[PDB]
Length: 135
Length: 52
Image (tube, rainbow over all chains, first blue to last red; front, side, top):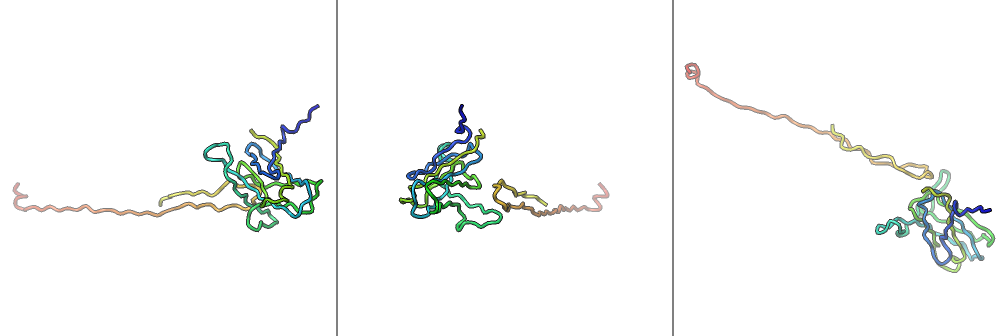
């Protein structure tokens, strides 16, 4: 009777309106984000993407946050400052969800947090999905 | 000729990046040397050399 998918496509919380939780992508070879809003916004809310590096003291503890660099495509343009960001537009509705991801991995951990902390930033929930274990 | 170094060119990069990076080229050098001179002299006396 069971059709469990949590064994093949686990999910973890990355932002919940109060705290950002580093997520681990070392054991997986694909992943993506997922944005949902729980109440009407006042304006667009931008997010900054970070990655962490293994700490020197402990081989299994995230280090300090490092900004993720941009990666322009063939027919396209780069970001104003060469970094990567995602902005949630004001047109979004409470009953919709949005998906996005970065083209490259960089560090073994990943994270996301708003550019500023305010009332609007608390209305968004961010989740990270994996797509397969390699170990 | 002396081949001091070979350098490294390639690297592992993401698939999204359509470009490629520039490495560090090798380093060739030229050298040279010399030769040296060994010299001496000795003298005799004809009468003694003939009579000995």
